[PDB]
Length: 270
Ligand SMILES: Cc1cc2oc(=O)cc(CP(=O)(O)O)c2cc1C
Ligand SMILES: Cc1cc2oc(=O)cc(CP(=O)(O)O)c2cc1C
Image (cartoon, rainbow, N blue to C red):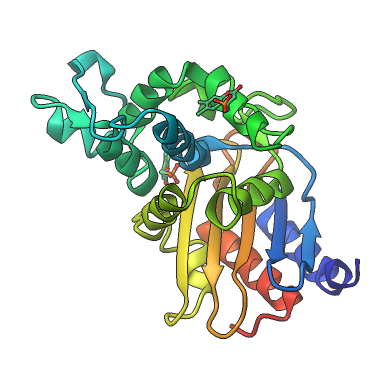
């Protein structure tokens, strides 16, 4: 409770300047200390579900040897706006592992939908999240409909706390077997879409893996990350935003600033 109180007022001022709501949960995996701000409210996942999607693929690969190297062929009708990798392999197909890397590191929408199909759709990803003990996460729709970010709509949402707890289980805990855990971490470390979010708050000498989400409406965007500061245990954190009006713009700078405050509250000099 103490650390959450240290940064309560700065968080309130930051979201007031932003003009919306900011939700943050950050966990120091060494001491167990946490920082919360609106950490139990639901926020739209936007593309951030794609990280958990890749983890679910990795979990299935523990039971289905050769899943990762399976080729997937698809037609032009599988392409979705913002499919930067999968459009370049339309005429050849891609493997499940390549689709997973594209979904994580480029937020590729066609790749995400193809992998959702393999796992049984939104309910199948939700079922995987239930299997690791996450009772908050829900995915309901596909790309791009899941980005609607309608105020008060619980579809395609989770909470910053549940996102962080599930991220910890998959990247540092025992939810995945050791080889799959490191592959998930490696995919997150190679993300290309988050340079202006949590990574902007993290010194250059720290390792970081993250997954972004941007809904394109309602000031709604997010990022979650595992951060390895030098000389101490890793930090896991999630920063989610939303705003009341459809035309409100998200802010990457606000996400970076919220990450800075969370790390400061935890006592992580950065
Ligand atoms: C995609 C997926 C969905 C799942 O939904 C479940 O209800 C239970 C599990 C764990 P399992 O029973 O297979 O050990 C589960 C796993 C994956 C990858
Ligand atoms: C609708 C939409 C807007 C986006 O605007 C961005 O600025 C960044 C991305 C990639 P994301 O941050 O979601 O990983 C993005 C994705 C979608 C579907």
